[PDB]
Amino acid sequence: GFKQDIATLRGDLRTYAQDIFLAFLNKYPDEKRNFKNYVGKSDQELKSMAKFGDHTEKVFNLMMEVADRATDCVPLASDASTLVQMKQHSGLTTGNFEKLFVALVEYMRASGQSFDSQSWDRFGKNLVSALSSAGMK
Ligand code: HEM
């Protein structure tokens, strides 16, 4: 289930974080307008850049924490607040997060692996809700 999925992802987090993030950027190309530095680069080019590997792992490090602290796929309000009030997210709307989680769910559904994709879908929607509550547009 969800909890084990957290453990699975953590067991190879750099690889999962990059593959999921790339799935997100490839599905929603318009989203690269939040990451100018990634434009015009193939997946392999991105994976070899320093800031890509570093930023994305750090994203998933915290995502997994937020996931881990959730109850029944409902994140802590404190965690939602943190994500909203991060300077690096000044721009974002919940739509950005929505898309990330659609790609994440899609990735999991197409993997050979018995991820609990329905729980990640709930998690994504509940985080979006919590981010709305904590003040993100
Ligand atoms: C649960 C979801 C997410 C978590 C946990 C998260 C977490 C983080 C963290 C920890 C950083 C700092 C990384 C660093 O600079 O070392 C970061 C930076 C950033 N996040 Fe998020 N993030 C999430 C979703 C998103 C989404 C959906 C977007 C845009 C669609 C986004 C855009 C950014 C940008 C633009 C930066 C910094 C600039 C860059 O390095 O590209 N984040 N995020």
Image (cartoon, helix red, strand yellow):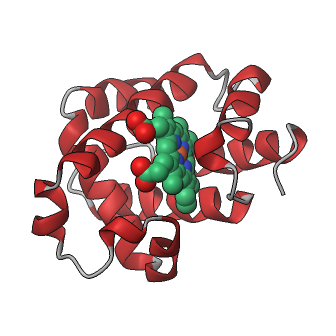
Task: Pinpoint residue 97: horizontal percent, then vertical percent.
Answer: 61, 56
Task: Pinpoint residue 7: horizontal percent, then vertical percent.
Answer: 32, 23
Quarter that holds the C terminus: bottom right
Q: At 73% from the left edge and 35% from the top edge, which residue is drawn?
A: 85
Nearer to me, 110 or 84: 84
Q: At 15% from the left edge and 57% from the top edge, which residue is drawn?
A: 47
Nearer to me, 122 or 21: 21
Residue 35 sits above or below residue 3 on the image: below
Nearer to me, 30 or 35: 35
Q: Is residue 109 left or right of residue 68?
A: left
Residue 85 sits above or below residue 4 on the image: below
Quarter that holds the N terminus: top left
Q: How many marks?
A: 0
Identity of the residue furthest to the top in this view: 69
Snapshot quadrant of residue 13: top left
Taking the image as drawn, is residue 73 in sight?
yes
Taking the image as drawn, is residue 120 in sight?
no
